Length: 430
Ligand code: HEM
Ligand SMILES: CCOC(=O)CCCCCCn1ccnc1
Ligand SMILES: [Cl-]
Ligand SMILES: [Mg+2]
Ligand SMILES: [Mg+2]
Image 1 (tube, rainbow, N blue to C red):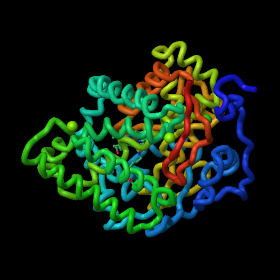
Image 2: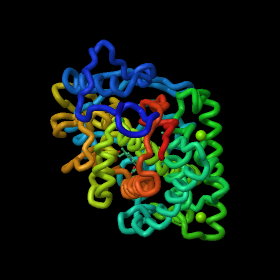
Image 3: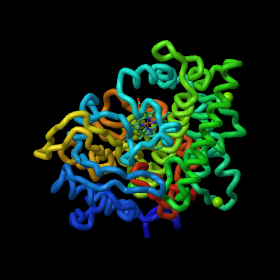
């Protein structure tokens, strides 16, 4: 007989640690592990932090991908932070997922995220101004207009007061914003959404499991990027695609592959993780109603810490991979030049060596040095200011229009080692 709406999901006792998981039951290199309940996953990373803070795992092989060599998993905050801040040792080349890069993949996935400096920073500087706090602040009106309309439409479209948060708010809000920043016409936003979803959801049968489909999607978005870039070359617009085609690095314009890769990076990065932060945030407010109440009764005062706690809690990017350029030793584990190293942000963000009470979802948490946007340094998330603003506005519009919005079913969770995703989240309101 809990308070609230009759079909709301069960609440949880805030602060309860999950049971730790016997190490023999942990297989980071099997998709089956990524299908387990998030409580079991959290307890497994707790076991690793305790018993095997640096451990070795085989690489998963999604259909058509090349697994290649295995990887050393860094599950402690300090090691993820150290690796992030030493890119001369922990290189982002040749890939930031664990699979091997191939020439075929590099045509579409060869952006600055898989490069070291100086070339990485010369590419990043083409677009960095558009993502700075003061420039992102100027698009508050666009974020608010879109979020307000989406929440209003949830109400207008659903006489029964039941909706899917993902398709009706969390997905379409960041999609609109990044597509408008890129200069993509509204008629194509839903094609961009589907392409994003396949690129980042590959291996989940609800998204795609045929490598031919992954490659067709990659080629189609790459061709879309090229064609839009060609238009902007001839007639400039005040959009990021125009910035990309007009730029020079080391005195040369970007090639077609560089344009395609940069466009794909920005549009794919620019929507799915923010979508998932919003959905995980609504799930957390549903499980921890006292946190909802405290945010709703001081929205602007708590918003800066609340948004960061949602990102720490959700850790929308589970890991990033690096490749060693020289031998090292961490925690008595020798690792060799050329070895793959995986940085588990999801685990760093529960590390009791860094966080007081890591199992408490605390929207006032301060300080909150989470690694949800990475450990800092050269590749720190370009979109962090944009994501923070989108998350804040989405929750402010829910608070104002449907303050008792609550999840009514447990999420359908994306099957992924890389992205902590929710495919559907049914919600209701009064
Ligand atoms: C809550 C949402 C988001 C999370 C949790 C997130 C997380 C991350 C993480 C962990 C990295 C890697 C950092 C590193 O290697 O040190 C990253 C990089 C990146 N993110 Fe995000 N991101 C989010 C939203 C966005 C948005 C909205 C964009 C907009 C386009 C974006 C664009 C990028 C780009 C371009 C990079 C590569 C930066 C570089 O290589 O210099 N992200 N993000
Ligand atoms: C993996 C296949 O897609 C790519 O290579 C391009 C997008 C990479 C996104 C990396 C994850 N992310 C999302 C938001 N900030 C970071
Ligand atoms: Cl939760
Ligand atoms: Mg419906
Ligand atoms: Mg436009």
